[PDB]
Amino acid sequence: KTFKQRRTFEQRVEDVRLIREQHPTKIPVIIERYKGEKQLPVLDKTKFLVPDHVNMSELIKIIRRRLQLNANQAFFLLVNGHSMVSVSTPISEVYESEKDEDGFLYMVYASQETF
Ligand SMILES: [Cl-]
């Protein structure tokens, strides 16, 4: 069902290596809906190539637009399994510290702070 269950570790590593070769300025991001989530919709895809200069505040705005949310729908994003300490950090810096061993950056979204 989840990305890590659909693709082998070998397959995920090789896909991150191809993104380095073909899209060298992009961060490879996996974005999934929390398995408990009732309110927010699912995304149209799983794997996102994010320009490495955007900060987390802008990435939250990008994902809200992609989900076509309105102003009073709540949205919380986990990175590497946990809350973001700051939304001001450039995603290139977030990637270097929070990347998975497969080389993806894993994010999960919910309408409650309680995942
Ligand atoms: Cl690129």
Image (tube, grey):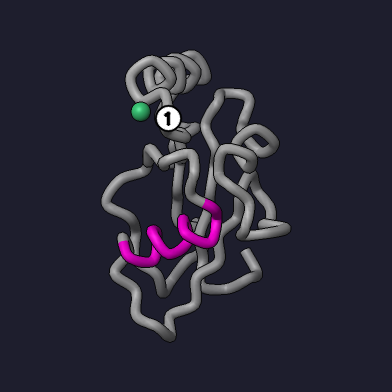
**Residue at image coords 52%, 31%:** 104
Farthest front residue in view: 53
Residue 108 in view (yes/no): yes
Q: Locate residue 3, reporting x and y percent.
A: 44, 36
Q: Quadrant of the C terminus?
A: bottom right
Q: Quadrant of the N terminus?
A: top left
Up the image or down, 47 lies above or below 16; here it is below
**Residue at image coords 43%, 20%:** 20
Nearer the observer, 15 or 26: 26
Q: Does ligand 1 reach within 8 Å of label 1's beta carbon?
A: yes
Ligand 1 is found in which quarter of the picture? top left
Q: Which residue is mark 1?
A: 25
The region drawn magenta spans 55-65
Farthest right residue in view: 85
Up the image or down, 68 lies above or below 62; here it is below
**Residue at image coords 55%, 55%:** 56
Q: Locate residue 28, reporting x and y percent.
A: 45, 33
Up the image or down, 40 lies above or below 52; here it is below
Nearer the observer, 17 or 9: 17
